[PDB]
Structure formats: structure tokens, C-alpha cells
Image 1: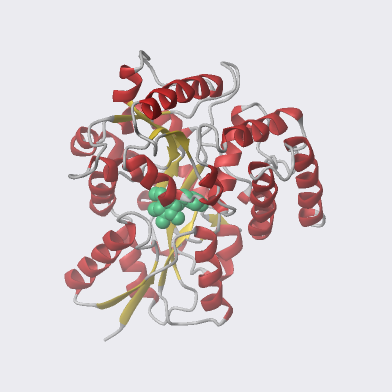
Image 2: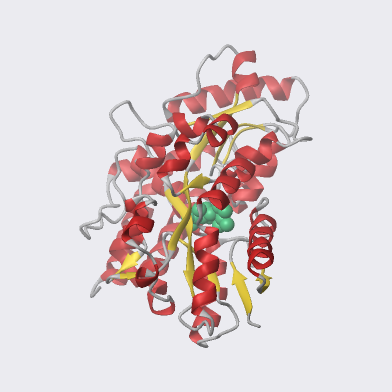
Length: 402
Ligand SMILES: OC[C@H]1O[C@H](O[C@H]2O[C@H](CO)[C@@H](O)[C@H](O)[C@H]2O)[C@H](O)[C@@H](O)[C@@H]1O
């Protein structure tokens, strides 16, 4: 009978690809359907290019794709409309914000799978060691704590120790980190939901300058090459006081044999001052049936299974990834394993989105502009003032007649 083929997640990022393949095989065994898993590169923007090869070809060789929250507006022509396959009651079990994000010109492109928000990981043993009782609330405090703990850990002999790691590589992850920096300085959303390109302002410029000031000082010089896993591996070996990353890193850090197990917490990222808004960039993935799938019925069944309560629960318990069903955030087993899901739920709900709705099918070009201009500041090629002006001009060209 049919072979249902799935491309989504990567075995290069934590346990996501291995776990996704396991869930697909479980569905296959449950329903007596043959399945195949096709691996993907680590970085979301590389995945988009890979999947676009299949879509350009109208290829029937993948039935189900795991698609980034930033993609519906780009990928909608390649998605089977799921709306007729779900009842209104079924759809209401997901956060309405994500269902709305996934709906493009009335087409439900994809089912919400897991959400995501940028958070601050911090070594609580080290905060205590150095006389701090709370994680930092402001970027200035983060800097002061990092300098002090670094001075001490280096003096004690850990020459590998850094104050802060984050995603500074030129790719989509840096758009995520940079939106957090800019927004948390009161510098706006880069492109506002109304279309206004707002990034050329002194608060956004300050945010980028500040981040440059970390590189080679509290963060490794090589941070300008780090994606999620490069940052996580410095952190997880016990060599960083702080890390900006997504929820998945938590379960990995708690695993048996992790050097940092039991030694860290998570909190909202810092901000410039008490009246700036908190910033956590909205992430996460959705489940799309290919418009080119020869087996829509079976592929829809698989996507419903993957998005189900018990598969999302398993994702939360084992991989510390955030459900897209509000009912899971009150589940006793989810909460006992991840108590921070409760503490940060409002951070997750107030996550700031990248400008994917407003940029639509042009979002990838906009983000490339953002990450290359931000990167030119991290590398020291440009100051923030010049980079936000140059970025404004680039985005104006991209979106001109959008
Ligand atoms: O659970 C974390 C996931 O990390 C990646 O996805 C996040 O980071 C991307 C940027 O690098 C965002 O565009 C995305 O929205 C985030 O969810 C990774 O691509 C995933 O497969 C991981 O599960």
C-alpha cells in the first residue's frame, strides 16, 4: 500500500529528528501504513531551500512537511487546505493565535505542532556562588553578572568559561535573537504589523551596538558562527553563565550525564529598562500536507496524529518543547516535569513575532536582509547606526510594491 514520507525537524538539532522519526514510525505501526522519514539540515532557512526544491518540482516524494511559523505566507500554494478535514471543535483545541498564523487567504496551511519562545537560561549554582539571588532583569545586569562570574571562573582555572552564548551566525536564528534585542530596547518590531519599517531608530541601533560589545568580551569571539546547537554545546559543557535559546535545551541539559543537570533555571530575557517590553521571539513548527501528495487522506491522518494530545504531551515531557494545546499546560504530568511551563506561560503568550505576516511570501528576503545587517554589526564591520539605516533601505526595496 502507500508509503507516507515525512520531512520535518533535523537529527542535527538535539533529539528532534530522532523523536520525530519515532513518532512517524509509531503512527505507521498503529495504522499498518508504511512510512519513511527524510532528514533535513539543522537551520530552518536551509530547510526552506531544500523543501522549495521539492515544491518547485511539484514532487510527490514527500507527503508531510514540518514547516516553520514564519513560512505559511511563503508555502501556502504548496499546502493542502486542512480546513475541510477538521471540525471547528477540533481546531479550537489549539491556540487561536497559531491557527490564525497558519491560515493564509482562508486556507488552513498546517496544524500547530509545537510553539517556541526565546528564553534566558542561567546557571543558578554560579549566581549563588557569586552572591546574586535572582537572574538579571536588565541587559546591564546581565553584563555585570557575566563580567564578575567570568573573572572568577577564569581565575579559578576554567579557561573555557564565558558569560553569555547566543545565536550569532548569519541565518534565521540571528533574526530571532536580534528581534529580541531590538524589541527589548523599545526599538520596535523591525517591520511593524501595519507595514511601517521602523528599524532605523536609535533604540534599535543601541541594541545592536550592545550586542557587538558582547563579542569577544562576555561571549566568545566565535559566537558570530553559532546557531542553536553551538551555543547549547558551550552551555551544556558548563562553560557559560547565561545562554539565550529555545525550550528544547532544557530537557537536554537535565539528561543523565549532562554536566549541568540540576544547576540551571530559565526566565524571561532581560530588557533595557523596566518600561521596555519583554521580548521572546515567537517560534515553532506546524504540520503541512503537501499539495503534491498522492495520499491526502492518509497524510492528513498522520498530521492529526502528530498534533494530537498524547504526541504533544510526549514532546513536552521528553523534549521540553511547548504544546500548541492550552489543555496541556494544565496537565499534571507536563507540569511536574516542566514546572517552568507554568511560570513562563505568559512569556510564551506574549511572544513577539517576526514580520512574517506583513512580509508574506517575501519574508525570507526580509529576514536575510535583517540577519546580514545585524551580522555586520556583530562582526564589527558596521556600527548599529549605519546598519539600521542600511537595513531600512534594504527592506524598503524588498517590500516596495508588496
Ligand atoms: O525547538 C527549537 C527548534 O529550534 C529550531 O527552531 C527554532 O529556531 C528557528 C531559528 O533558528 C526558528 O525560525 C523557529 O521558529 C524556532 O522554533 C529548529 O529549527 C527546530 O527544528 C527545533 O525544534
